[PDB]
Image (tube, coloured by chain):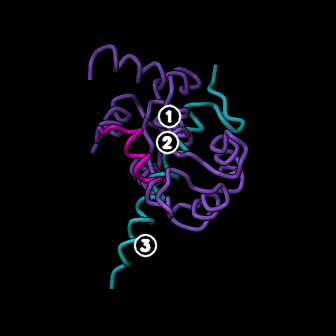
C-alpha cells in the first residue's frame, strides 16, 4: 500500500498502543482491524490471535500487524457483497426482510449475534419503524462516509 | 453428506453479515463503542 495508507494503518495501530512501546495486544487486534475496514469472522480473528499467542506472548508489533492485515487481503465492492448476502434471506424476493426474520437468522445460524449486537442492528436497520428492513438502504447508510 | 443448496448459502451468507455487522459497530461507534482518544 502507499506511504499515505501505511501512515493511516500506523495512526490506527498507534492509537491502541497504550504506552507507545510499538506494540498492541491481542485484545485490541479485532478492533484495530475493524476500524480500518476489515471484517474478520470470529473464527478468523481467533486464528490471528492464536498466531500471535503461538509464542506465549500476546503483543503485536507494527510489521506483524501489517503482515496480518495484508495476508489473503481480498478487495471487492463491499456494499454489493453485503447486499448480496442479505438478498439470500429475502424470501419473497422484494428488497425487504422483516425485522423479526432478520433477528431470527442472525441469532440462530452461523456466528450468532448476541442480544446486544442484534438489538443494535434492528434499531439501525428498520428506519421507517415498520417491522421491515429495506436492506439496500440499510447497507447504504452503514457504508456512508 | 453436504448441506442443501439454500442451507449452505445461508450459512456462508449469515456469517458475512455477522462479521460485517461487528465491523460496522466499531467503525460507526454504535452500541456504546468509542475509539480511544
Q: Which chain is purple?
A: A
Residue B35 horizontal side relative to residue A68, left or right: right
Percent x, y for residue A32? 50, 33
Magenta extent? A76-86
Percent x, y for residue B9? 39, 65
As helix, strand or loop, the secondary structure at mark 1 comes to helix
Percent x, y for residue B4? 37, 78
Find chain B in the image and tell me its colour: cyan
- Residue B3's label in the rendered image is none
Determine the residue positioned at 53% across, 26% down: A17
As helix, strand or loop, the secondary structure at mark 3 comes to helix
Magenta-span inclusion, residue A79: yes
> Which residue lies under the disc numbered 1?
A140
> Which residue lies under the disc numbered 3?
B7
Q: CA distance from mark 2 to mark 3?
A: 22 Å
Residue B34 horizontal side relative to residue B12, left or right: right
> Which residue lies under the disc numbered 2?
A136
Amino acid at each position: 500500500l502507499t506511504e499515505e495508507q501505511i501512515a493511516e494503518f500506523k495512526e490506527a495501530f498507534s492509537l491502541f498502543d497504550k504506552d507507545g512501546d510499538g506494540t498492541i495486544t491481542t485484545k485490541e487486534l479485532g478492533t484495530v482491524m475493524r476500524s480500518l475496514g476489515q471484517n474478520p469472522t470470529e473464527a478468523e480473528l481467533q486464528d490471528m490471535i492464536n498466531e500471535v499467542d503461538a509464542d506465549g506472548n500476546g503483543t503485536i508489533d507494527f510489521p506483524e500487524f501489517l503482515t496480518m492485515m495484508a495476508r489473503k487481503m481480498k478487495d471487492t465492492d463491499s456494499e454489493e457483497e453485503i447486499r448480496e448476502a442479505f438478498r439470500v434471506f429475502d424470501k419473497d424476493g422484494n428488497g425487504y426482510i422483516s425485522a423479526a426474520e432478520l433477528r431470527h437468522v442472525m441469532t440462530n445460524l452461523g456466528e450468532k449475534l448476541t442480544d446486544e449486537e442484534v438489538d443494535e442492528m434492528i434499531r439501525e436497520a428498520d428506519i421507517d419503524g415498520d417491522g421491515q428492513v429495506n436492506y439496500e438502504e440499510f447497507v447504504q447508510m452503514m457504508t456512508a462516509k | 453428506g453436504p448441506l442443501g443448496s439454500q442451507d449452505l448459502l445461508e450459512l456462508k451468507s449469515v456469517i458475512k453479515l455477522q462479521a460485517w455487522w461487528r465491523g460496522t459497530m466499531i467503525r460507526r461507534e454504535i452500541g456504546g463503542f468509542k475509539m480511544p482518544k
